[PDB]
Image: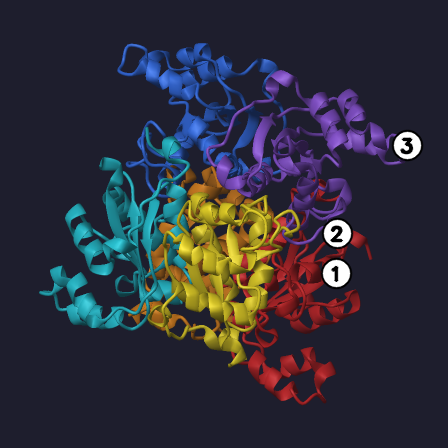
Chain colours: A orange, B blue, C cyan, D red, E purple, F yellow
Amino acid sequence: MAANKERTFIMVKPDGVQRGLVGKIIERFEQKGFRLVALKFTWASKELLEKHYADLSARPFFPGLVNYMNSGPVVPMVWEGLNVVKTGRQMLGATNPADSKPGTIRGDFCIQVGRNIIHGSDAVKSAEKEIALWFNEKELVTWTPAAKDWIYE
Amino acid sequence: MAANKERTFIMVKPDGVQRGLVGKIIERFEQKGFRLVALKFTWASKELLEKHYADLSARPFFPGLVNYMNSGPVVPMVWEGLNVVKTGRQMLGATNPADSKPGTIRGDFCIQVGRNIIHGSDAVKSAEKEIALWFNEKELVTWTPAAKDWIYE
Amino acid sequence: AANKERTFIMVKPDGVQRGLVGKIIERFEQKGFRLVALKFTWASKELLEKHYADLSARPFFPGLVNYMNSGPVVPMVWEGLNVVKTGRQMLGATNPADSKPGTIRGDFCIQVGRNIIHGSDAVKSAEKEIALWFNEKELVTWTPAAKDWIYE
Amino acid sequence: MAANKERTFIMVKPDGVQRGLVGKIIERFEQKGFRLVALKFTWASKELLEKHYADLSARPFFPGLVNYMNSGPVVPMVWEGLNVVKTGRQMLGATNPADSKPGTIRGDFCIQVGRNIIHGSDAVKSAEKEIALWFNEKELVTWTPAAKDWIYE
Amino acid sequence: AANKERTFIMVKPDGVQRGLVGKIIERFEQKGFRLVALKFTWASKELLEKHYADLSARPFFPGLVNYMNSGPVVPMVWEGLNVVKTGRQMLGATNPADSKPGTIRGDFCIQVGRNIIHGSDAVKSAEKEIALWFNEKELVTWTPAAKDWIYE
Amino acid sequence: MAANKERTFIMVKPDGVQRGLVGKIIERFEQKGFRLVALKFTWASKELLEKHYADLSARPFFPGLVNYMNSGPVVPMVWEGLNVVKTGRQMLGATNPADSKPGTIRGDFCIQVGRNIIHGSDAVKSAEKEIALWFNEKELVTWTPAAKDWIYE
């Protein structure tokens, strides 16, 4: 419940892996002061993707979206810190890269919304759901950064 | 006329060359996913510069502008991609660097509007004219990036 | 004189601890701003109370002074056109949660009491801060080779 | 057996995670052209560590080494490519950072051998063993980078 | 004249494809070397056979020519003290497996037939290469503001 | 006399300042894990410079050297850590930048030996003398990095 212990789900999409952006994305979160909680590299099954995108099941683009997200591997992650959900979204930039400003991940590194390299949870509740979908609890690491008292009041 | 095949004219100005920013500027376009079409290094004639800046010929300190832009070599370039004209301008930042936001090229690397290191076309129509002014069609390279299908849907 | 405006920028104890001194300096150098003064020091509470005198009516004032006295800092002076206002823009909003990506605070820190860097908020406060942290002898005058490519 | 499909085990050690080097290390391998095969974030058990370091079981420093490696989380990874084992070791630099040259991971980012931020397999056979210790086969991802034919003859 | 030595450096098709043009240019700029000529072009096999004439006795010559004709390249000329020899050192060993971290090839590529960049191996071959790829009209003469801080 | 508390003198020379390398140089020391102890920006007197370069007073072009080092401001620094004198020199690279390897400071950023951007002490004994020459003891800051126990065993 503690503000500083909020968690979000960030995922490098197949285009982000293909284009060599995994390290650069992780570095953005590390240098900011956010704390890694979970990390893996996986080819997501259509089953998992259909759960992740379940709200979109009736949309005409849904099958193509699932097929695309199943067309190469992804890097799911969990990050922890104060307002990491909303601040994470800020760091990512607008969902449509056209509107993402320079300095943001999407603003610096991609062009078109269907190839927008990265996903971040849009709310605390959706983050909790996404974390539970993509990770089991034993994959979530609890640790204490040496720099903690220089990052947080 | 294909949206993804739009081209813009980007030029490193004499101060950008002098201050060692050519590579950094090209890198920003490459990492974004835009496609290089043309590139050269040249000392622009006053004649060419007067055509490029024709819109300013009846405004203050035109001979001064032309003389300054003829005082050192420049790096004219052509870049291709979806909305590259508008997005290019966004990447450059506001023309006056005090208004340019951090993260942008002008925002990060210069200070004063008459020493603002870079130019980008302001519209599709002016891009077509600028490209034709600074390059011959034989200098425009046709090629296909390996990563194309991870940049564009 | 316009191009000779100066501002006070200081890396805070958390900026030093988290290894951001060079990165911060690099941001001002690459922009075209000119270094005028630089040092590394543990600031006394007496000095810090003067530095933050404008905030003395605020509940967080003693905590700010105590915190800023908990590790060393890197006071600096930078010179150039509109460097106070532009400096503030480069630093980003005082509260990092509101600072945009691309700014120093937006890229490198999270919470306002650990916001890594200070910059003067106006020409007048810059003049005050520069005089507080430095002797005139420590302010170096010189001219960058690139000056005519930065200013007309 | 194919030369280009050789794999090695690279692990960010607890000090490397603590000091915010995970993204930077991954970026070194991505930018080189090597291909990510597996990635995770974990607190290694003493059981696993005693298997990883089994050859050292009789050494007087063994218990302290295991305790230290169990004192914070690590980032185990697998990378694929031509001579990735030996070239990986080259990229890491000498095991003792004192002897690691600038440009290498250890040369750029650490000081003392007991806090030397990273591990890489020292031979193809030891890599195969380490990969099997730290990962299961289902965690190893097979995929094809768009850039493959620009990285390999 | 010593400080006016020139070498030919070219980003190969794999360097262009993998988005390394700016990074390569930046390495020479930050070193203090001076850009003299730059372009982007698809090279003909006729040109490439002349460029690689020294290697015509080798079994890999036709494959090298064909490969170098498979995508566009970025030919360049750089100027400065011992730029041919120092350029080669910056590029790293021709075979990337032998190129050390810190060099262009050591940092950015893996296999010798995909080794991203070419640099002249001697003053004489540089003179030949510069004349092959550029007209004298394309070689720009100018003087960097920082010159006196790079050379005495 | 503690090994880990060794200190060296590092100075950005006038060309390093002029060419905008101060931050980059400091960053290389920070990222390595060395500890900043002292830092200033000053225009060095000929008197001070003659003491610093006393060993060269009977060698060619001494007045020229002194005049050049008095032609622009410098950034004197003190850094602390295990074998920081020797490792510092390794990080700087060979004194003549043509011999300095890529990855080193001189290797990456300069060309000619009399314009070689940086100085580092050549031994523990010369460091002690240089530190005492350029700084007062009151300017040497005592502090403890949060990451110390992840840098040193």
**Is the Cβ of the residue at disc 2 closer than 8 Å to that at disc 1?**
yes
Mark 3, secondary structure of its residue = loop
Relative to residue D77, is residue F18 drawn left or right? left
Q: Residue at x 51, y 59 (%)?
A: F54
Give the residue displayed 52% in from the left and 57% down from the top: F119
Q: Are marks 2 and 1 on the same chain?
A: no
Q: CA distance from mark 2 to mark 3?
A: 24 Å
- Callout 3: chain: E
Near mark 3 (Cα within 10 A), the count class, few <14, some 14-19 or many ≥20, is few
Whole-percent x, y for residue C82 in the image: 25, 40
Crowding at mark 2 (Cα within 10 Å: few <14, some 14-19, many 20+): many
Looking at the rendered structure, the kind of residue marked 2 is Ala
Q: Mark 2 falls within which chain?
A: E
Q: Are marks 1 and 3 in contact (CB under 8 Å)?
A: no
Q: Is residue F28 above or below residue D112?
A: above
Mark 2 = which residue? E97
